[PDB]
Each structure stands twice: as structure tokens, then as C-alpha cells.
Amino acid sequence: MEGLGFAIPANDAINIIEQLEKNGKVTRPALGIQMVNLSNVSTSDIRRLNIPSNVTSGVIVRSVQSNMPANGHLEKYDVITKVDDKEIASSTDLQSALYNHSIGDTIKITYYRNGKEETTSIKLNKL
């Protein structure tokens, strides 16, 4: 009967020489990806897509960082047409808007590959 354990925390070497002023975690947010509009939102992009109407053209990735998200979540081209339930057209427009309002906020990117709809959730890094 009965039972005694330990209830003792980890060791403490105490070896710090910096006051710092920030936090830290395992996985952090990222959004350092370069993209470009299909063609400045033109009729040519419409036919290239399939049969849009509410979107009309969009943005396509052409430079992934460490090919992390492109590893599978998205293709090399990654043609995103929707972002955070919002319509886009130019990488500079969506990038500026995102970095403008809602800092460090999480958004959902919706792209299409060979007529195959594919959406993924990604969190933008603040500061």
C-alpha cells in the first residue's frame, strides 16, 4: 500500500548573460514568399485558369523559402486565388494588405493546381 514519488523539477545550471526582452517557441510563423500576378489581371489569365467569375486572375508563387510550404502543401507554381476569405490579384497587393492590417494574424490561402482545388492554413510572422 501507499506510494512515495519525487515531484522534483529538472536541473538548473543557471548560465545566462542576457536580459533579453522577447519570447520563444518551437515552431514560428512565416510569410517570406515571393509571388507575382498571373498577368496583371487580364482575360488571358481567365482562360488559363478554367472558368472563374468572382475571382478573375490571382497570384502565383515563384520563390519559396526553404521550400517548406512547397514541400507538399503547395506546388512550385502555387496559384493562390483566395486569401483569408478575401479576393486577390497581385502579390504586392495581398502582401501589402496583409502586412498592413492584422499583424501576426493567421490567414488561409486557397490555390489551384491543374484544376485541383487545394487550400491550406498559414500564420504570418509579426515583426
Image (cartoon, rainbow, N blue to C red):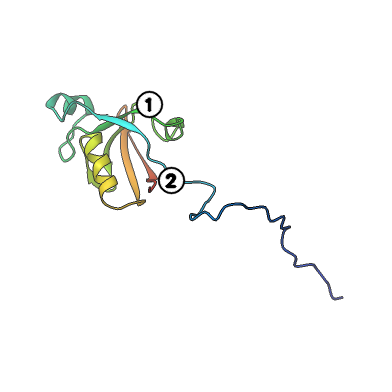
Q: Residues within 10 Å of mark 1 (few under 14, many from 20)?
A: some
**x then y, percent, for residue 7:** 75, 67
Q: Nearer the viewer, residue 71 or 24?
A: 24
Name the amino acid, label 1.
Lys
Residue that mark 1 sits on: 76
Residue that mark 2 sits on: 29
Residue at the bottom extreme of this rendering? 2
Residue 1 falls left or right of residue 20: right
Q: Nearer the viewer, residue 85 or 94?
A: 94
**x then y, percent, for residue 41:** 15, 30
Q: Residues within 10 Å of mark 2 (few under 14, many from 20)?
A: few
For the point 34% across and 46% down, the residue is: 108
Task: Say if 23 sits above or below 75 in the image.
Answer: below
Q: Are marks 1 and 2 in contact (CB under 8 Å)?
A: no
**Res 51 → quadrant:** top left
Name the amino acid, label 2.
Pro
**x then y, percent, for residue 74:** 39, 33
